[PDB]
Length: 241
Ligand SMILES: Nc1ncnc2c1ncn2[C@@H]1O[C@H](COP(=O)(O)O)[C@@H](O)[C@H]1O
Image 1 (cartoon, protein in one colour):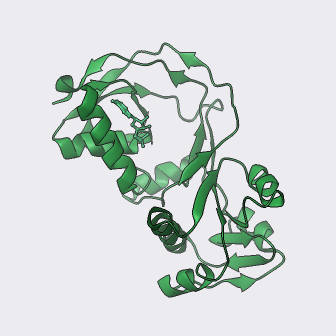
Image 2 (cartoon, protein in one colour):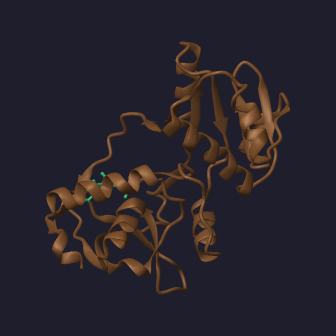
Image 3 (tube, helix red, strand yellow):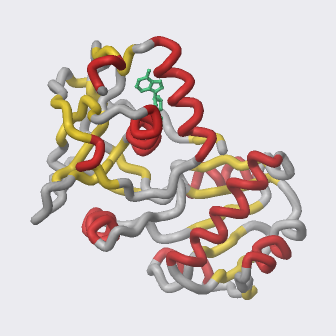
């Protein structure tokens, strides 16, 4: 899937990194196999690791939440590496926000209404669907020409994501992940998109809770807006083993 986000000015800041052991880092999303493979291919190609992990200390545990860096972490593990350069964030600062992504596609709601129904889901026509989704009462609202409620919670969200990640890689839909619901609705009006999937965004406390339960969200659940991007770093891959 293709990210499609606004032009946020987020400043680069020169924040030093520290090496943290990979087995002390906890993911909060399922991995995308394509992203993992691409990182492995890139890092082995140059032998430079230039983009630190962004981490948050798990309260009460000798562990860190991966805020940004799931595929770097997993890819380094698969290569046999032991650590990664990391920037530790003040995650519960008001300066850090968490939003979600809005999976939107161009296509027909037929190979998708039925192919979600094959994974085991319901799709009830409901004018209040988006309203219910945003209060966190259903798994997804599905909005385009009509409005549909997809009942459930996390297990159901993972099924909706699953279908789409497969069909994207398969190439029967064009899957864009919108940073903003309203941008999807613009591109929808223009005809470039047909439907959008709307769930309530997780809170920071929920992300931390999920991690402490040893659980993960589906891909593209969190969209963290951070007060800075760390400047690039000069770490050799050989330093990570
Ligand atoms: N040589 C490299 N060192 C560090 N990060 C990289 C390298 N090549 C690609 N990346 C990043 O690896 C990330 C893999 O996804 P994630 O770790 O989930 O953000 C992407 O954000 C890429 O920008």
